[PDB]
Image: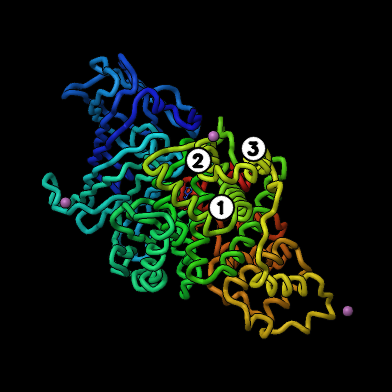
Amino acid sequence: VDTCSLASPASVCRTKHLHLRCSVDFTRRTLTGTAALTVQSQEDNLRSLVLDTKDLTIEKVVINGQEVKYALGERQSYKGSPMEISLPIALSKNQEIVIEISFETSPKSSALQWLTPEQTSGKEHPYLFSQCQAIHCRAILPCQDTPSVKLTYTAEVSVPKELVALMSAIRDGETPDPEDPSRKIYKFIQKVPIPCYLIALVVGALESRQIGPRTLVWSEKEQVEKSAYEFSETESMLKIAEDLGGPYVWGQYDLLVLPPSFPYGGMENPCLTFVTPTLLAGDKSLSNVIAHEISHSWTGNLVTNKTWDHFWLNEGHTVYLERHICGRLFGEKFRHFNALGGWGELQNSVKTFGETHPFTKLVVDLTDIDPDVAYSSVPYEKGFALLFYLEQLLGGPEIFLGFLKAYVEKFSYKSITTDDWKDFLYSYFKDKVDVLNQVDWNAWLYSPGLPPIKPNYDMTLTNACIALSQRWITAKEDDLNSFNATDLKDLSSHQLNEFLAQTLQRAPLPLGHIKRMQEVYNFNAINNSEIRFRWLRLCIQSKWEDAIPLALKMATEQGRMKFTRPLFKDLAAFDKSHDQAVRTYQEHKASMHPVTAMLVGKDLKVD
Ligand SMILES: N[C@@H](CC(=O)O)Cn1nnc(-c2ccc(Oc3ncc(Cl)cc3F)cc2)n1
Ligand SMILES: [Yb+3]
Ligand SMILES: [Yb+3]
Ligand SMILES: [Yb+3]
Ligand SMILES: [Zn+2]
């Protein structure tokens, strides 16, 4: 059962198609229009159905050209309000009907961020973007807001003519709006069935540059050139991902570089991956995020988790595929380095929640839990650790990659549970069932904390990071003069980041050590968002007051939650910056992404 949805489940009825016709009004901060749902009954004598909605204004519901009775139930917190539709005629099993719902979004839709021109690069035009994952599609349109249901979609979007609309679909033309010549209509088609959290929309002053045979990069004009360079390896990654997962079925693989308030590193929207502008390091060093989003074209978008309790199926397999792409491009020692880094991020998450916390379990129970509050590195890294452990136990990467491809083939276009995955693993590895029966499944899948077994990792690229970090941690005041810019000469940006991660795990360090690190390494000058984030966290946790304006600036000038949430939390925990952290959040709250605003609010205990 999907405990995050209030809609009729897949066993009652299934949405087969959505035909969306809407208009974006920037003055009212509203999306208005019709969502035409092609619903197939899965039951005999079906006379009503329930849809998920959240802060939607419903005008009418039309079936067979006539208005039908509908009712909106009491709001159930983050789940929204259930919408019961009275069908005009009882439906037999497998019978299909079209339900056209006239709706309007609230300006406070948790799925959307409305940007004023001042909040964009260009400063002349407003901007809109959606983020439906996990359960925010119900805050845009009435739907069965569950990944257990997959549907195709077509969309027609009216926007002011000076702007461009894009969706998680194939672009299907543009025309002047026949109802308003100050507007344009942008058309879209998604022929591959998808869960509704993969529905996405962006409206802004967008420009494009071709960077591959099936890839355009999209952003405001100011970011196009930098984005084209940063993501130039995209086609190479797609070719490797196809070799590992089978055919790319989505047609196009475009990239959209969002404004800095985009709350995640990326979003695997089909045909149009969304990315944070914090990836624009200038040297392609944060491109693993692209490898991760590309990998989702197989794991997550083709093979989907049936409910959000099984989310690890989505991320664990994606991180696994992502690390193989980087492994093919830069070698097996690099894949091991990234895997070990991943284990360290898992240690961090387990330490933050506490080793007995229910969110440290691989398979979770989201009954009465807002998925946004549960979000962490655990399904990513505990999920990856399991697969990497299975890879070693079952004979190596080549053998395990054979399983990955067969798993994708077996479950493409379906929504599955952990039991479905485990059953297939046992079927594929029938000749190694004795090895599989040695796995402590109850601990790996259902127990909190660190996994019962840690995999084996090649140390070649990690050794220099640990050695430098340990030199700083063990150093006394009279050893600080020995550090010099030459200590970093043989370290890649990835190794610099790992050195900071290792040191941050032992934070605080004495204030004199942090001051010396800046003196000799000039970390303040580094623009790479990952390195800068860890360096600022290290400064704040080591109580360096000079870092307060830098940390406040980074936390607010961008909104990627991975950075913004721990920076605000570190600033709130430092006595010297506590008041500034709270006040800065209060003054920025209204201009923030709604999900980021909620979570920073909870982290700071500011209601
Ligand atoms: N897809 C990513 C980027 C990427 O990985 O490529 C972007 N992204 N956007 N939203 C989310 C997201 C995912 C799960 C959420 O909820 C849950 N979190 C943990 C568990 Cl165990 C179960 C849940 F349901 C809430 C939000 N992820
Ligand atoms: Yb066409
Ligand atoms: Yb079985
Ligand atoms: Yb000494
Ligand atoms: Zn992912």
Q: Residues within 10 Å of mark 1 (few under 14, many from 20)?
A: many
Residue 583 visible here: no
The x and y percentages for residue 216 are 30, 64
What whole-number distance in Å separates the C-alpha atoms at marks 3 and 1? 36 Å
Of circles 2 and 1, the one toward us is 2
**Residue farthest to the left, as pictured:** 178
Which residue is the site of mark 3? 446
The x and y percentages for residue 160 are 22, 53
Which residue is the site of mark 2? 424
Q: Residue at 39% of width from left, 52% of height from top?
A: 297
Residues 561 and 466: in front is 466
Helix, strand, or loop for circle 1? Answer: helix
Numbered badge on residue 2? none
Whichever of labels 3 and 2 marks the residue nearer the N terminus, that label is 2
User: Ligand 3 near label 2 (Cβ, under 8 Å)?
Assistant: no
Count of numbered badges drawn on the protein: 3
Which residue is the site of mark 1? 585
Residue 439: image quadrant is top right
Q: Residues within 10 Å of mark 3 (few under 14, many from 20)?
A: some
Q: Is residue 529 above or below residue 142?
A: below
Q: Residue at 33% of width from left, 59% of height from top?
A: 253
Of circles 3 and 2, the one toward us is 2
